[PDB]
């Protein structure tokens, strides 16, 4: 009921890194404090590292196990955006803002970081556990994918959106907004594929899959809180970032056809500013009664 | 999570194999005691409250000055003497969220249910204390519910119009089209739904003063009207809603229908403009015999005959149109058009179907004009005359544009009080007052028709609730027997009250003398046929209440001949969307869609069982989708024979039913005398 | 392939290293003797031709009835005595495809060039045989060219209006917005381009009768107007063209500009509506100082001060608005807004830029009103007063909506004939007659302003053609010296003709006594500064033609003070799009875009060399894209000082130049006194 | 030395079939004989099948086994083109020219056609035989992919090109030329990757790999001959198409770094004929003159 519509929306959102000139960001970058520059670098590396997993494994593995030519095509398109567009865009932002040696060090740090690794490996673990012709394991991986696309990225997206909403780092913020817009539709689409599997299950199996999804969400959420304090306490933003994580967790759940887990909260206004039944002919005698 | 929201959510928690229906009384009690009594502004005396409301631009001093404060105090005493209690949480929630007067910052509550009812009654009575007390008793007993505009806005300084349904005729000219856009925006600004007749507009590819193939047709006007309604969005509060009607024999009928397709181009699709199709008996006859039909270019017909195509009887004039070489036409397949209609209704619920000859064969004012189209809710069926809006320097020729005042009898409360006559007459008086006090300064045809026709719409609701709470199935013949008797009585007493008002004021409606009321042709079926119940169970429902007989109808006919009739139109059954919750009633005469209504308000989900739902009457509350649409058609046609205007008839369809099934339902509705079909709702 | 277009394509075949320019003479000769004379309806005598045209609704009998047929015959002899020959294929092709009268089936040709000119002259003269002969001599010599509406429709029965530029002021009300939509559709139906001022409309998020955040802003009205212009498209042959103007200090300025962005959504973007931005000197000063500017909510200013924001002087009230707490304002960066304007003009050519203080520091009728917006072609700059369209039952307060009749002098042919005075006076008389015979009966303010102001627009074309054919570079100081002298002389003789018309008719334009003509301040630079050519090369171009001195201007000032002026506005330089081909002239006073212009008509490709282009003047015909826009600004500002209205000033940009270069050109135009900037055309 | 330039070339060649309006072919299609229309539909259906498998299976699987994020980005982009652009374009052509029943019938015909099933079996079999960290199985699949890109498509491409060259079906032909332009660069790129693996081998191993490549080519060739006769005999063109496929077989071998195998022949000359402004901030000095 939905793949051709998503095909259309995906291909009409096509874009390339070269379209946004990045050099003018140096005019606001130079005015940020060390903690602001440090947080931005670390957040950016976090997003880059997670998105690489999605391009190399997450999207291609789902495309491999999903049946249907049109679904495979949409999924291929999404994998292309991760590897050919998003990955180049993140690299471009980095090369503009930091010298080569600084980029290498930030990636070394974020690669060793406990909270980034915990979530990255949890997601990758579920992708590696998909078994041929087993729709339960596929569903679990789709849940992981939706959580990455619609939830885990957002502790990171917060900061570029925060600057973007203030008139700072506008070129890289525009790029991030385009990336985020792609991840949103990726999350919704994979969510619909997961609901299709979920709806084929018994009531007991459904309850079991719901417990899986909520348990996974809880593990990721508790690690996100730690990840958040680790990055954002030094710039005083953690309270507001936490509200943004919960709001996006609720969107991820709704993508999977589940109820929101967290109470509704208002979001930081600066970040907000950044953000046919069946045709049958009449065969006569239907006009007579 | 609020305590009342939790209590309302315990209904679905099944205890001992049954829903906890009694939790809704606890839910509403908790809602009141914890939120309403806390957020209700209280004053030491009623005088202080009234002074605060008038001086702070909440009420109108004009209508309140008509009474001494003692009379207003006694009216408020009468309202509070009933000690009215909302039976369900949803009733109180809907009232205090939609109709209760709030502060300018929408933080506190000024009006309780009794205060709102007292103010509405004092506005209705227009200086009469006993009449105001009678209105208070009628509304606090919930026998009669004024429409959402009247109930919400009566006696308010910053109020919209008390009328929300308007029907405009659009003439085939740029001046008239621009005036139609202006009037549509002005009426949508007031908060009223606007229906436009586009049948007079010439089709696409017609000549404009010797320049052939220059007209964009009705779809360009449709786009103009859609943008006009989008702009006039009621001060950004509620989305502007409008309707467009086209005759099925109009050449642009296929383009008219293509505006609602899901694949429609953005330069063709209209979003905020509902569409209704007018179908004469000629089209159904052509489709029945599978003869290839013709759609006509209206301007060619106007040039050939001097009359608009929709102003002429298609049954007699269709052959003359086809045989006339100077009339331009294109061949169509009427069965294919019917299948396209059914497909569109399955996909989007559009268009509304108005059976032109079903309306006009029983229309009492055919001398004034035939009924050519309906309103946005497909129940207003009145004669209209198109206006000739000329150039700016010239004088316009103002016609008649339809606008009627809505009110609903609560069938359950009227039946339990044995007060059909009194409720009908008081509702007629209130609707007459609303008609007289309505003055619209930017729709000259609407104002002229309101002053001349004095048409009102008195509907009914809680039919399914009353039947299910009395152990009667909606599709049962006993239900149709009750509907027949009840609406015959309603028609009798509305005609009697209208004739009494005409006698009191010494005036009838304009061009009454040509109506079937004046000639007595209206009363033929009433002086010839007896409409008393044919079932002992139904006849017991009317115990203690005089059912009008043939002799009573003859006396009414003589009275109408002697004294005339004040209202051209009296009865129309509107959908009654949101006022049904406040009245604890099922919407209109339609059957219930769901036994228990699941809705989400804010971040909290709410549960609304149908009024009177329990274990004993669970299966009498049969859902509309589970019902046989033929029997629903039979019920509505039983009611329709006593309603002078139309009835908002929604088709409730299953997902498994075909296009052929929807077409069969439409054709059986046409066969049974159904005037209009509102919506195709699919489960 | 047609023989004439085959000959016309031999121009580009370079023989001996040169373009074969003489092929276009053979091309037009073949065009005539193979298409035109064959397809021309020829009558035995002119009497039969005129009777045939009058009887079959081709001409108007009223204007032809003021002459005896001997006089009409004499006029036609005068037209044919010249034996005019089109010098290029494009001239004749454009005439016989756009302006020549054709049979009702568009099959044959009824009018030649002489026939059309004679009919236009007899229409202009209004019964005078000698005046008709003078007009025939003026147009057959191609010294003066009536605008496309006048030249196309003069004397035709089934015709549009002779005026195609209309300017409407929209008041901040729904009645006024509806009337603006209606009038826009009425004027687009007549074939005219309509410009609307949207500055008085309150911004998005303003209150509509004490409910806040209710107004949709100027973008909703923009969508309404865009659909109104799409509807009134005149068969779609020439779709409805509208322009919207907004003051840069309006709060909706960013949303107003976002309607032209390529990435705009379908619910915001307008396609058929051009946009212009009115920039007071205050905004340029704020951007120059890099200070923080403020856009304002117009309704707050109107409530606080009782006047609309655009009716007030921003250079004196901006600080008061900022300091006023009851005025609502939004902080913006003026330099960012300027950069956005430059980017939007680079990517789409929009908005039109009007420098309001450049218009109003020399505006002669500031007592009536200040100029607040321009037309669709961005050259009409006249005082307007907004109308107050009230409810249907109430009387409307009719203001002044701008409209002027266009007409262009051919600088080359006027200078060749040494007839600046006679051409200017005869063109003024013809434009006065067109103004007097124009009667718009569906635009009350346009009608009232046409009757009261009596404004005309007398433009010029072939400036670059005349300079290039005289060995003068467009950017050269000699070209600006010639333009100064020529347009000073044109202004002198237009003022003289206006004063003579006022003396003869005994009436001046409404509120003339408050104008600068009456006070004599208009003539200060003319009685103080001599405008005789400063170069001997230019002075020989005016040899044999008297150049008014300071003494002549003093005498004219005394004459105007003692007799008054008939026209509030007289001179405006329009783009003159398609009549430039017929007159074999370069478009307006702007430089040429291409030396040889290549066009495709249907499935045929044809080339148009610039008039008089050869090898001896190839490099004097410098393309507009290759020249410095600063020197073009200097030329237009030199011309603008003698033009009371504006000049349609197109900016010709290369791909290499950035948005900073466009902003620099705009700021230099503002510095040099440029009133309006029309288009940012990029190659 | 080459991936970056292929990346840039691939992304700059990006297109969608919707860019080309197809209603212009309606008349030249109507005018073809029933035999011609039948061959044309079947030819494009055979192409659709090849692109379906190249997009679903071939390109993603090669992407999985090739090392390097940039190489993977190119291969992912090529995969997307196969199924999201190329395979879909054929449906755009079908939906314009043919009624639904004829479309349904031709897709049923691909399922039961023995030559089309054989070629899919052979190519996809090799893709699915790739073993992780086994460069020889990867080489074999890359040879198969080059043979699909640069040889197998051409029995299909012949006919749209043959019409394009006569000024017939030129809108459909424009789509096909865009597809062909893509496959040419896809065949070169995969060829270069195959050569990388081949060049790592001993002389003895190389000799075996050439045997594999030539044996596979001959086996595919013999099947393609029968397929060509089956499709083209009814339009009289089988011998001409055979010359064309031999020509392209040589190009496939060359893409693999091997010598041409078939002798040169004259190809039908008809088929040969078938082949914002920069934003600069305002300075203070810009406001004075
Ligand atoms: C009615 C209406 C008005 N408007 C805007 C457009 C007009 O410029 C502006 C004025 O509307 P008005 O027609 O003047 O409304 P009003 O007179 O009742 O309000 P007020 O007392 O403030 O004058 O409101 C909308 O945007 N949408 C609407 O639906
Ligand atoms: N006191 C009071 N009465 C209110 C208010 N809103 C409605 N009423 C009704 C209740 C009574 O029926 C009626 C008179 O109330 P009152 O003025 O307190 O009267 P009384 O009992 O002192 O004579 O007004 C209100 O806000 N305060
Ligand atoms: N005969 C004729 N003359 C035409 C026509 N259209 C324009 N004219 C012009 C040509 C002459 O200047 C003028 C008089 O032409 P005529 O009526 O033939 O007169 P005459 O040649 O007998 O003096 O009218 C036309 O169709 N026929
Ligand atoms: Mg008319
Ligand atoms: Mg107002
Ligand atoms: Mn990504
Ligand atoms: Mn993604
Ligand atoms: Mn491909
Ligand atoms: Mn390929």
Image (tube, coloured by chain):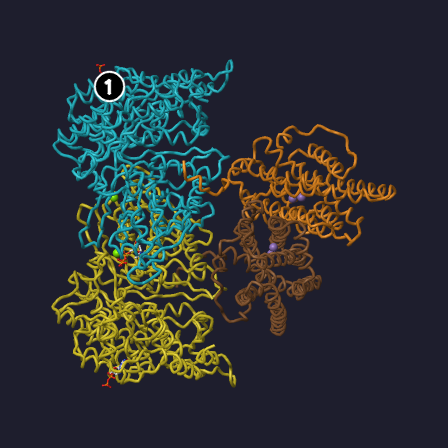
Chain colours: A brown, B yellow, C cyan, D orange
- Counting the numbered discs, the total is 1
Q: Outermost residue toward the right?
A: D204
Q: Is residue C244 visible?
A: no
Q: Nearer the viewer, residue B479 or B375?
A: B375
Question: Is B119 placed left or right of C291 in the picture?
Answer: left
Mark 1, other Cα within 10 Å: few <14 / some 14–19 / many ≥20: few
Identify residue for label 1.
C546
The chain that hosts pointer 1 is C
Q: Quadrant of the C terminus of chain D?
A: top left
Q: Nearer the viewer, residue B232 or A229?
A: A229
Ligand 9 found in image quarter:
top right
Provide residue B378's location: percent of width, then percent of height.
33, 62
Numbered disc 1: secondary structure? loop
Please determine whether, in this image, residue A261 is positioned above or below residue D83.
below
Provide residue C141's location: percent of width, then percent of height.
28, 19
Question: Is B462 placed left or right of D111 in the picture?
Answer: left
Provide residue B488's location: percent of width, then percent of height.
27, 73
């Amino acid at each position: 009921d939905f793949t051709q519509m998503f095909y259309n929306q995906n291909v009409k959102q096509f874009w390339l890194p070269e379209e946004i000139a990045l050099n003018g960001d140096l005019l606001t970058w130079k005015y940020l404090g060390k903690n602001e520059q440090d947080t931005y670098m670390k957040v950016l590396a976090g997003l880059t590292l997670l998105d690489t997993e999605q391009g190399n494994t997450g999207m291609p593995i789902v495309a491999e196990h999903v049946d249907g030519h049109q679904r495979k095509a949409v999924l291929n398109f999404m994998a292309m955006m991760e590897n050919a567009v998003h990955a180049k865009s993140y690299s471009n932002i980095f090369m503009t803002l930091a010298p080569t040696e600084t980029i290498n060090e930030v990636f070394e740090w974020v690669k060793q970081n406990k909270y980034l690794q915990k979530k990255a490996q949890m997601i990758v673990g579920l992708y590696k556990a998909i078994q041929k012709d087993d729709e339960i394991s596929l569903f679990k991986a789709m849940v992981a994918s939706v959580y990455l696309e619609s939830f885990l990225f957002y502790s990171g997206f917060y900061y570029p959106l925060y600057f973007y909403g203030q008139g700072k780092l506008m070129q890289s913020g525009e790029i991030i907004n385009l990336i985020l817009r792609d991840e949103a539709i990726h999350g919704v689409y994979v969510g619909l594929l997961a609901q299709e599997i979920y709806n084929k299950q018994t009531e007991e199996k459904k309850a079991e899959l719901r417990e899986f999804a909520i348990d996974l969400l809880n593990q990721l959420y508790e690690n996100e809180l730690e990840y958040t304090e680790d990055l954002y306490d030094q710039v005083g933003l953690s309270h507001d970032v936490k509200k943004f994580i919960r709001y996006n967790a609720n969107k991820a759940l709704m993508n999977l056809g589940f109820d929101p887990y967290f109470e509704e909260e208002d979001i930081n206004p600066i970040v907000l500013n950044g953000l046919k039944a069946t045709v049958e002919p009449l065969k006569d005698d239907d006009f007579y009664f | 999570v609020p305590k009342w929201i939790q209590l309302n959510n315990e209904i679905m928690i099944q205890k001992d194999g049954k829903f906890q229906f009694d939790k809704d009384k606890e839910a509403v009690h908790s809602y009141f005691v914890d939120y309403i009594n806390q957020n209700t502004v209280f004053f030491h005396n009623l005088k202080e409250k009234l002074d605060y409301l008038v001086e702070n631009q909440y009420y109108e001093e004009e209508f309140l000055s008509l009474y001494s404060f003692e009379d207003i105090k006694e009216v408020f005493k009468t309202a509070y003497a009933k000690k009215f209690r909302f039976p369900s949480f949803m009733s109180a929630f809907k009232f205090y969220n939609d109709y209760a007067l709030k502060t300018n910052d929408k933080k506190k509550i000024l009006e309780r249910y009794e205060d709102r009812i007292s103010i509405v009654a004092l506005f209705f009575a227009n200086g009469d204390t006993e009449k105001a007390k009678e209105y208070v008793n009628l509304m606090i007993n919930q026998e009669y519910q004024p429409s959402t505009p009247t109930f919400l806005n009566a006696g308010r300084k910053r109020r919209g119009e008390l009328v929300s349904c308007f029907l405009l005729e659009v003439n085939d000219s740029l001046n008239d089209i621009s005036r139609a856009i202006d009037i549509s925006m002005q009426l949508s600004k007031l908060g009223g739904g606007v229906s436009l007749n586009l049948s007079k507009l010439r089709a696409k590819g017609e000549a404009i003063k010797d320049v052939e193939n220059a007209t964009k047709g009705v779809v360009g006007v449709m786009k103009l009207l859609d943008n006009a309604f989008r702009y006039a969005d009621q001060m950004g509060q509620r989305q502007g809603s409008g309707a467009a009607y086209l005759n099925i024999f109009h050449r642009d009928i296929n383009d008219f229908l293509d505006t609602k397709k899901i694949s429609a181009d953005e330069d063709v699709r209209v979003k905020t403009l509902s569409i209704g199709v007018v179908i004469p008996d000629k089209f159904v006859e052509l489709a029945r015999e599978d003869k290839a039909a013709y759609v006509f270019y209206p301007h060619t017909i106007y040039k050939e005959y001097g009359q608009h195509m929709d102003e002429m009887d298609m049954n007699e004039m269709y052959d003359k149109f086809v045989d006339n070489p100077r009339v331009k036409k294109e061949k169509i397949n009427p069965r294919k058009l019917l299948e396209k209609l059914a497909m569109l209704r399955s996909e989007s619920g559009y268009p509304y179907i108005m059976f032109q000859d079903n309306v006009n064969k029983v229309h009492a004012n055919n001398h004034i004009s035939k009924v050519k189209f309906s309103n946005l809710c497909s129940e207003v069926l009145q004669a209209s005359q198109v206006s000739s809006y000329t150039d700016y320097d010239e004088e316009d020729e103002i016609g008649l544009d339809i606008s009627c005042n809505l009110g609903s009898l609560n069938i359950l409360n009227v039946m339990e009080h044995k007060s059909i006559e009194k409720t009908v007459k008081l509702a007629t008086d209130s609707l007459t007052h609303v008609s007289e006090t309505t003055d619209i300064r930017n729709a000259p045809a609407v104002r002229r028709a309101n002053k001349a026709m004095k048409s009102i719409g008195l509907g009914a609701m809680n039919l399914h609730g009353y039947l299910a709470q009395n152990g009667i199935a909606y599709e049962s013949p006993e239900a149709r027997d009750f509907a027949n008797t009840f609406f015959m009585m309603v028609n009798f007493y509305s005609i009697q009250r209208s004739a009494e008002i005409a006698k009191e004021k010494g005036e009838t409606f304009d061009q009454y003398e040509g109506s079937t009321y004046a000639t007595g042709e209206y009363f033929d079926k009433y002086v010839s046929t007896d409409f008393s119940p044919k079932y002992e169970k139904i006849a017991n429902l009317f115990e203690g209440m005089h059912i009008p007989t043939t002799e009573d109808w003859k006396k009414l006919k003589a009275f109408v001949a002697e004294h005339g009739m004040y209202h051209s139109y009296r009865l129309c059954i509107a959908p009654t969307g949101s006022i049904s919750y406040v009245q604890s009633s099922t919407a209109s005469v339609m059957p219930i869609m769901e036994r228990i209504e699941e809705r989400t308000y804010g971040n909290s989900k709410t549960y609304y069982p149908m009024p009177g739902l329990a274990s004993n009457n669970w299966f009498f509350y049969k859902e509309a989708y589970d019902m046989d649409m033929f029997k629903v058609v039979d019920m509505i046609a039983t009611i329709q024979q006593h309603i002078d205007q139309g009835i908002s008839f929604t088709l409730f369809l299953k997902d498994t039913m075909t296009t052929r099934d929807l077409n069969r339902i439409d054709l059986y509705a046409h066969h049974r005398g159904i005037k209009t079909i509102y919506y195709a709702r699919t489960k």
